[PDB]
Image (cartoon, rainbow over all chains, first blue to last red; front, side, top):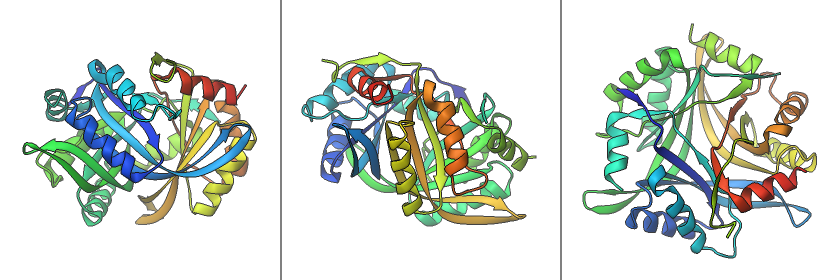
Length: 107
Length: 108
Length: 112
């Protein structure tokens, strides 16, 4: 059954290469910063240093808790300190009982 | 025109194969439980069976109403190939008048 | 660091829509950034399933995500109505509840 959730978080960030995204995903799950991470290839168009840049990137979605969110975000940045990556956080408003428990238990 | 919305829902889950995702998408729409379903190939990383898994999967996003959400999650749980399905629901805070109307009308 | 710091945000918006082809998505993304209506637009290929004319349709499409502010959202949407290839576009808006300080600043500055 669905249950209201206010403690789960989805952190959305991007990295340039598939290799980095795979490495970051595995390491974040190993460190207990995220329970699950998805990687999706994307094209991004954005304003950069005055110009319009178009680039192939990897969109990452980290499934975590509010308790781990700050630490996860800091940690990701430490992995590419030269970068200014996307960093957006969503709050799911429901989940299943079982999926929320799994996610919490994972961390 | 943009309108504020409180009644629309996106339910996210994943399945293993494109075939599975297609069949599940079509059955949800035929059941009147979602107006539209998108499928996107992803790679997933999570801890399972004492190991770190990396699997190719299909991300699904079901577009529905709050009225249909419970019935959709129930039906998913019965039909879903995974022993623990992903289940995350987001609430859009705005849509267009036309698009909201289309979504709700599709689930009459 | 502003790169290392989350902050609570109520002013950012993600507008989600779809278009038929990669070419249309690339043109629309570029035009949107040039207009200053979005700071960043991402494009992802998807398949969509929905009922059309009474029957189930499956279509390949491009999912677009436009990163913008609440101040530009109304104009972005109005602009998309005029420029969008479909006569009834997908339009779903989400509100991120946090961001990094650096990303929020980059975003708001891009649309200033």
